[PDB]
Image (tube, coloured by chain):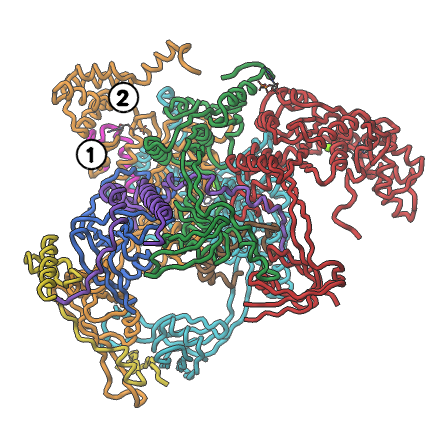
Chain colours: A orange, B green, C brown, D purple, E yellow, F cyan, G red, H blue
Amino acid sequence: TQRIASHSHVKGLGLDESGLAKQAASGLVGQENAREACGVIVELIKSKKMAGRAVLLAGPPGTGKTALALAIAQELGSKVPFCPMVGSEVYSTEIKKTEVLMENFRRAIGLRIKETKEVYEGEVTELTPCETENPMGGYGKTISHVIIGLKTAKGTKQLKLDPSIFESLQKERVEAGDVIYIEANSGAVKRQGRCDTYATEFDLEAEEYVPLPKGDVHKKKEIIQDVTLHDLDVANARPQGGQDILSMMGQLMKPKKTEITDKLRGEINKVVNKYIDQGIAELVPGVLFVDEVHMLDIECFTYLHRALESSIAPIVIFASNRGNCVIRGTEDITSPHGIPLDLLDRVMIIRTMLYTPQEMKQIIKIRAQTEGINISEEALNHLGEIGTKTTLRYSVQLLTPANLLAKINGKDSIEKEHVEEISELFYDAKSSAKILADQQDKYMK
Amino acid sequence: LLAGPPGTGKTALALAIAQELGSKVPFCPMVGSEVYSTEIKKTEVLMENFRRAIGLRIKETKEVYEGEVTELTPCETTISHVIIGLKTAKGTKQLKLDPSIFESLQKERVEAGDVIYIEANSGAVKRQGRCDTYATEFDLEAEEYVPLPKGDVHKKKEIIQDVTLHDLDVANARPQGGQDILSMMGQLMKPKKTEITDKLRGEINKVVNKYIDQGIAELVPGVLFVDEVHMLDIECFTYLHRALESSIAPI
Amino acid sequence: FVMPPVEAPPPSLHACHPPPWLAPRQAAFQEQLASELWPRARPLHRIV
Amino acid sequence: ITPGICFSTASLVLRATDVHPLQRIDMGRFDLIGLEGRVSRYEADTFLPRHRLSRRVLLEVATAPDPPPRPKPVKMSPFYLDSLEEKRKRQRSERLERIFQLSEAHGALAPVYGTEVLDFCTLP
Amino acid sequence: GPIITYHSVTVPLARCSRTFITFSDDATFEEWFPQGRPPKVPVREVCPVTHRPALYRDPVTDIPYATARAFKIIREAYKKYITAHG
Amino acid sequence: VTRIERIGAHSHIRGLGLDDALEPRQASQGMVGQLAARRAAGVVLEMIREGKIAGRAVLIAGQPGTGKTAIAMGMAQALGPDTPFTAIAGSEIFSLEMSKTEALTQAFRRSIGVRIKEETEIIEGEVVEIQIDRPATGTGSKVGKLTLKTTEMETIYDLGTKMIESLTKDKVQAGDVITIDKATGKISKLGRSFTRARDYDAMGSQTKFVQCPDGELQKRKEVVHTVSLHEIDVINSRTQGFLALFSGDTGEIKSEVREQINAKVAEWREEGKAEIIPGVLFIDEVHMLDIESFSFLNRALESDMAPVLIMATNRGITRIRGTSYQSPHGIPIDLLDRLLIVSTTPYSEKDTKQILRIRCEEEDVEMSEDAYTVLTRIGLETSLRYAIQLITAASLVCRKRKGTEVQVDDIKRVYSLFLDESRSTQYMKEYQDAFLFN
Amino acid sequence: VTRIERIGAHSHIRGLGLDDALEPRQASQGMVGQLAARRAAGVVLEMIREGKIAGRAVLIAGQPGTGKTAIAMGMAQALGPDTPFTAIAGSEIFSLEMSKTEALTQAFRRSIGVRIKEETEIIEGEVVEIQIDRKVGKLTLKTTEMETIYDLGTKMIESLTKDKVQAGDVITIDKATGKISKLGRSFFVQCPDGELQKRKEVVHTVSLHEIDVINSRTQGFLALFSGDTGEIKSEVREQINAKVAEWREEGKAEIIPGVLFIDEVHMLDIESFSFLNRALESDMAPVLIMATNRGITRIRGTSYQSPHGIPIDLLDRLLIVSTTPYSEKDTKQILRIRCEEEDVEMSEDAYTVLTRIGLETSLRYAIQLITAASLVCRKRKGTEVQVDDIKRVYSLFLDESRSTQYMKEYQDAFLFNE
Amino acid sequence: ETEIIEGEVVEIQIDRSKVGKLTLKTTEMETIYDLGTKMIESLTKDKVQAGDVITIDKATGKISKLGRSFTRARDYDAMGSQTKFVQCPDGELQKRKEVVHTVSLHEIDVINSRTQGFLALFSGDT
Ligand SMILES: Nc1ncnc2c1ncn2[C@@H]1O[C@H](COP(=O)(O)OP(=O)(O)O)[C@@H](O)[C@H]1O
Ligand SMILES: Nc1ncnc2c1ncn2[C@@H]1O[C@H](COP(=O)(O)OP(=O)(O)O)[C@@H](O)[C@H]1O
Ligand SMILES: Nc1ncnc2c1ncn2[C@@H]1O[C@H](COP(=O)(O)OP(=O)(O)O)[C@@H](O)[C@H]1O
Ligand SMILES: Nc1ncnc2c1ncn2[C@@H]1O[C@H](COP(=O)(O)OP(=O)(O)O)[C@@H](O)[C@H]1O
Ligand SMILES: [Mg+2]
Ligand SMILES: [Mg+2]
């Protein structure tokens, strides 16, 4: 968080309340049309009524495709799941590509669970059965309640409980002076140790003595837990916590991703629907961002047709900087973004344009502000000129070397000379390519 | 590199180098097509052979107490120590054993009349049968009867054993023994070669350097001979570029 | 309901004069493994 | 139900890997993975460098008489042989040297990670 | 024989469920419900030498202490007591 | 609140929309047009429902966006949940855990359901009073008595030790409506007829009550157990197979296991124990299968346990994967002879407008007539899927400006914001050097 | 009764049919003709039996159906069961369990055996009375010549309790191990005659691969039956080679070099060939025999053409034995031998027709027609195969040439014609 | 930073195993401790006896054995592979242990990948 990454300045889409894109806002400069389209996509995600909708961000490299997707994620917030993914990740040594894609699809659909946990804490002061003056059957003693006195820091309360708790109290070996908690939703007694006030400095027990609970005896709170469908799928496919031989084998054997079946996923969907209907949970459909989609092969693209046509799928955002490239897995088949035309029919294309020199200068200034770098006007203009040639990424990468060089020289700002020296020290792709072409004999291969 | 037409004596020249060095210098012969394993990556095979070529010579004196058991008495304070009586052709010796050896003696099912040996440094016990003087105690038992040992009960031998860095690497790849359930079940798992970490390699290098400084270890760099090197692919050659530049690699 | 057509115990290794420590070691290993794992295999009784 | 396969082999084959202890070195001096979960950074770094035994202390304890019995809690030479005794004292010296050498050898290695590091890094 | 009877009934408040537990003999009732009195807080002992809160307890003298010097003084006093009383 | 299932591509398709004579209506149950293809799908659906002919293959072929998957989903919705319908993509058979033939075999066997119907004796009633007497100390025989009540009955049962243990584990109390199966002794609590005593603490908020069951106590009810052939194969392959039902990880099931299961299921069918419910396997984009997979399909359809196979492909004369051979639909001619082909013709203007209307109705989007005309023109010029996407895009743009009906201006705005394949390709040609590889 | 070993393709081959001077006979031990190939194979057999030279490689090359595999099978038969003869195909080294070099290493080590002789005491008799009391016990065993009572130890009592032994059972006991095997009951196997306790000399020939696998891990011998060997470490193999050398020097064991036969060696790739080039240079390498019918052909895994699909570097280490096509006389003699093997009686006219059919089409086609013609003759209640039966099976079953002609007639109806 | 108890074991008395007492000593101190059920079980599992030099973590109660003290009666002829003789610790029975180590993110990932994931840091079978 404290370290500054490449998209650390993107705090969202700089959109007006009417959806029009401001020239420079929220860390984004230019790309007004793409930003407006991404705002419409953000509204689509927030509406939560659409499934399997796909958006393709198409444009030359360094045009804000990843920045726009991250701005969408910022607009949605941390509540909405956002699963980034590169196309190269489907190639796994454990599971098939379609399984990786399906798992990433299920990661984007989130579920928020709200429950109230009501507990009674305290140190047991009293443990008294409530006998009845008329014993049932004539002989012996019959009990109708068990009074448990619970003491905390700021109170003491007595609880008239069911007689059946006498067995739980004996199983937990609860005596006076022990700290216990009773859960209302289950009616079970759990002994969380003995009070520390009865412990002497000469005792050696570790987990036996616990502090007297603070607060009130009756504690109730609302627990909000955020889970994804993939979490439930994985927890049910390779369960952890059993005491049978299969769980022991799972602990012993090396963990391995498996091809989760449609049966388990359908069961998870049924449980999620039951929770939603009961009011326990609220569905949070999020976004799957697949950067470098062109690295997917023809099998992945074909599977995406069925994946996107589903009614449970999230909203998928693709991104590709390729032109009329050859689809991977095929022999000499060319498509406009490295993506077969069947999948292009299922996506909405957002075009990202190149940056004018003024927008490049603005982005450089923003990046300098983010990195804590003071840059003079002449140095900024020179760096923008450097960015007109070469590329924008090259110019924004000279800021920290130039700042370091200035600091070594003993100056608190980047001057033009620092940028010139850095430009001399480091080469861009085009200059290196010129050197390589001029000396192709001396290089290898 | 030995470059020449087939049949001109490159392999013979390498074997002559090996003969000139002697059996004390590690000569690891490998064929270029041996890196295509189905368990580990090719670079792991190359690094394993590199570590095989580097040798370590360790000088150590071993002590073993060997003989027929004439008495086995644990001394209670729990057990403070175990007094054992071992018999050989040259006499009888009474030994005080660390109490941890009692578990090993009980596991090995050591009784009076059995011929055992005990390692002084480790406490390991091996029950190598019953003494043949008791062969007639029954007319039919499923026992292995062994002659009484001839020399002294206490045997000392100063030995020089050569090990390679790969032996130390593979010894630390998986745990040995262990009475836990996870450890026992791990013994049933099929033994598979693994991509040993560079952290483990460096730690083992540190241990080796410690013992070299102590003076109980000697380093023998050795030679790795790769025949039919043209069967290596471009990835193997690229990894060799880095591996040869190491300060730890062999010739 | 599916039953294997044939059922056999595992192949056994026999030597006239084996190392007298191998068999007891295997027996102890099996005994410990069974004592630790057989109670955990009871849920699978009906399948077997 | 079929009887198992009885595979018969030479008894010498089962001893192929076996090496006598007098013919092999102690590999426990290179055992790094065995220290994990058993040996801590405290023992290797802070305790042992301070509380390693020395030959002098070992000899002093061995030669000194038995300590006096711990107090109870209160609520408040005709048959003497010189050669045999020389042999016995040589044996005692060898035993003490062996104890020292083994104690140094058995605590020489330090864990790569140690119990504290693993416990700190091991989430629930 | 000596039994514990678990009883669940339907009784009018229009109906409610109640559970009762019946012990055949008073011995079982006492065993399951000893009615133990609340425990007593131990006295926070103090070292007689340094008056700091006690942290240790010399087994021979049963005198709590909180410093190595306090322990040495306690053992010296015990040695003097042995010499005098014998 | 939004359920896990939301508006997808084919959410408006509720069936094939045919009458009794299998004649397609112009617009019914979401389907519009495709009269010949829908009639053929209806005949195939009748063939599936009859369930007498094994290993029938149908190929739905047509241009992209002609409703192949719409017709398949309509068939699935018209079949109903009783008959299995396994829909997979062609790419899903390429697996690192199993062979392609094994994946196809499992897909085939997931499409056949085995149903066992048996009658069991069932006790359902309201617990009036439960009494359990157990020894105070040591092992002993628990003795108990249970009273159960309906609207017309009340019986007191003397309980055995195992029934006592079951009731104790289920924590059955008075007022609990319980169901008891006499054979297995399983007890299922289904509600409470009334509240627990109020004087108790730590009991929680009492839920709603359940009315007491009527009729006799011990009834006889029909229990139906339905599993697929794949589930039987998995649970019979190994002891841990039941966990493989959820984790996958079935490996490759032995052919002996499948032969034994085929024999046992045939025996059950002859003995009246079980009925076989053949279903459908739908492989979307079957052109991703290679020659080995197609060769397996050729012979796997010859089994009496094979389901109806429905394939969809939008390929013309194309190279078969894994070979250098050009074949119709990317499928070998040997497999094309074993199947009937259903062609889907392109949509007209009125069919496109009706599809757009159905999509707007499904998405709860209100649109003007001029907007419908413009959107239909855009769909004819670009594609049907682009216009469908613009429906909700224009809905969002209209809602942003505090409107109620999608106008032509909103459609133009989303047409400007979101591009089709044609305009994107044109703009990419305009900046061809800026894009990386051409 | 029908046993597992029925009549196969080389069932008539019983040896190489050579005299003491390695001069082949025209027809002997199931072999006909090919005097040069059989003489060379006999020389190679003498080399194998001598056991001095290691890693010698021989290639048997020739046209299809020229006795290459027949020569190999005769070599295997001339060697006894004592000498290992590992026969694999080139395709078998391609495995998902191990590498190709590992598969060939296991093939090589399976061909070298270690012969170890040891003495054991074996007790074989009929149980008369068994008594066990809370441990002590007695056991009474009898033969047809003597009876004895034994005082049992704890371990033998446990062994007899684990394997239910009652009076009347005929059992054999290995004294040192308690290995009790019940071989029947007597009052069904006859009771043993001679001495009850016998000292026997048991000889085991154990391959290097078996030693490596047994010592690879605990219970590792199971991998000898279920694959699952993985890739055995080179350290274990080196240790085993050293211990085997120690045994040979100390007289505890004898080395029995054997033969590895790789039929259709052209399936090997360049990696496998490169491994074979150096694997043959070890002192523990067996004699390698390979067979291939390939002419100048592409080596698998490369684009290079080589005379046998084998790279020239490996071919320089080989001695090549060439098999020549058979004549009319040799073809007829082979047909007669196969008829005798299958118990089929033919007329002389049938033999002439079948020889002409075999020369015109193929020897394997004619050999196949022997059984078909015999079945046709048995269908019409005949006893001797006539020319009519041969013509009937000629019409019923086609050869490659006529099948190709008919396919070319309707080439459009077939699938994927180039 | 962790609080520990460090000393040589003098006596372990367990009554009957519900309650018992443990006596620990240094060169400058000696005290007696009252044990509970889990402490007694942990001491019996590690087979801690007299003369053993041990450390006990106050927070978790885990016991690790550093070594054993050397007496005249412990002049063993054969020693186990883990036994080693150490001097009795000096100072105070209660001590603070500070451990500083550098690990990488990959190591923390491997440790938490499985139950005994630290083993994969040696094998590499991550
Ligand atoms: N319009 C913009 N406003 C602000 N920063 C931008 C803009 N476009 C790109 N950047 C930044 O420039 C860098 C280039 O990356 P990016 O544009 O995401 O490349 P691509 O679009 O090819 O993935 C990133 O640091 C990104 O945050
Ligand atoms: N200069 C030489 N002197 C003696 N023997 C040789 C010589 N060169 C080769 N040989 C022998 O001839 C054979 C071929 O040599 P080798 O080293 O295998 O050639 P390559 O260079 O192909 O490996 C081997 O048996 C080797 O021992
Ligand atoms: N005849 C139709 N009736 C209703 N909706 C249709 C029809 N044809 C296509 N659609 C819808 O238009 C989209 C494209 O049709 P689809 O079946 O996916 O084409 P394909 O033949 O490529 O599978 C889907 O959302 C589908 O539901
Ligand atoms: N010289 C021969 N003597 C006896 N039988 C032979 C002879 N040559 C070939 N055969 C037989 O002819 C058949 C063809 O096999 P073979 O000639 O070995 O095939 P290839 O040589 O192509 O591997 C086999 O039944 C074989 O036994
Ligand atoms: Mg489709
Ligand atoms: Mg052949």
Q: Position of residue B116 (x, y in %)?
A: 48, 51
Which amino acid, by three-letter code, is at mark 1?
Ser
Which residue was labeled with disc 1? A26
Front-lying residue, A169 or G26: G26
Q: Is mark 1 within 8 Å of ligand 1?
A: no
- Residue in the picture at 16% in, 68% down: A151
Report crowding for label 2: few under 14, some 14 to 19, many 20 or more residues within 10 A (C-alpha): some
Q: Position of residue F219 (x, y in %)?
A: 48, 76
Disc nearest the viewer among 1 and 2: 2
Q: Which residues are magenta?
A: A19-43
Q: Is residue F172 above or below residue B174?
A: below
The number of numbered discs placed on residues in the rendered structure image is: 2
Q: In the orientation shown, which residue stands out farthest toward the front?
A: D78
Q: Is residue B52 magenta?
A: no
Q: Is residue E69 in view? A: yes
Report the quarter where the N terminus of chain F lies: bottom left
Which numbered disc covers residue A394?
Answer: 2
